[PDB]
Amino acid sequence: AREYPEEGEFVVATVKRIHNYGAFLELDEYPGKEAFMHISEVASTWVRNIRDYLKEGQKVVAKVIRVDPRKGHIDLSLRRVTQQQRKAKLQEFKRAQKAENLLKLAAEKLGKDFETAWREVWVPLEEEWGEVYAAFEDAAKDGIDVLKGHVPDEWLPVLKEIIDNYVEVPTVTIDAEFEITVPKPNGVEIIKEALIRARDRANKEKDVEVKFTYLGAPRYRIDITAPDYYKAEEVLESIAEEILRVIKEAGGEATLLRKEK
């Protein structure tokens, strides 16, 4: 967005130069702008050798204690940064970090310039959404189309490709419950056996997951998790017969619940 960090941001910076009184670091997320960190901010106790903390090229997440744009001076802090504070950022960095390697990986297949892209997407996105990666992610879930109109039509095709390959495959899920009853001194025994048989059986078709949660005789609810409703609805009907049949053979009556005709 604007040129310099915000009063208070937790930022990431490479240890450019360091000496007696402090360290000059370059903000890895603000092309070129360089900031300063006093020695009185390296630790919560006066330091003996700043060396024991900083080292040339070292990356770090600090807190913009005070800043003046008109001059280009950015004063940084290491003290005020609790473990949470830190990883909180180290995260979003690592995050947008990938969101980058993906956009860059987009200029290579679309055969364009880094800047001539980073200005037509990385910006439209990190503006419409708040985060590029998230947009890429949500594109991977809800479908590439979530980007149409928002970025050039000539992009999408390459993106879908990239996204799908490096990002991850989102999945659907559905609940359903049965009324399974088996009159016999070991009905449970089989019921369980029954579901467990059926379960482990379906669970094998990688990209599927079935889970039987008991919830009070004679109900048991199944939680199918395929990669898309098509699948899911079909995996339930599979576990339909599978159950009904098997408990019937053992003299029971298992039924699903949804018919309503």
Image (cartoon, rainbow, N blue to C red):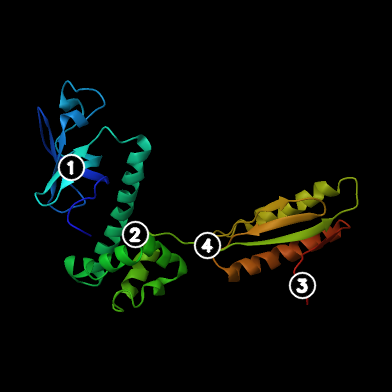
Real-space CA distance between mark 4 and mark 1, rounded to the nearest whole angstrom: 39 Å
- Does residue 154 sit above or below 9 in this rendering? below
Name the residue located 73 percent from the left edge and 60 percent from the top edge. 177
Q: Amino acid at mark 2?
A: Glu
Q: Considering only vertical position in the picture, is 258 above or below 56?
A: below
Q: Nearer the viewer, mark 4 or mark 1?
A: 1
* Quarter where residue 164 is shown: bottom left
- The disc placed on residue 14 is 1
Q: State the residue position of label 2.
A: 131
| Residue 64 visible at all | yes
Q: CA distance from mark 2 to mark 4?
A: 22 Å
Q: Secondary structure at mark 3?
A: loop
* Residue ID for mark 3: 259
**Residue at position x 78%, y 74% from top?**
260
Q: Are marks 4 and 3 in contact (CB under 8 Å)?
A: no
Cα–Cα span, label 3 and label 1: 63 Å
Which label's residue is closer to the chain start, 2 or 3?
2
* Between marks 2 and 1 in the image, the one whose residue lies nearer the viewer: 2
**First reached walking from the N terminus: tag 4 or tag 3:** 4
**Of discs 3 and 1, which sits in the foreground?**
1
Q: Quadrant of residue 242?
A: bottom right
Report the residue that reaches farthest toward the top: 48
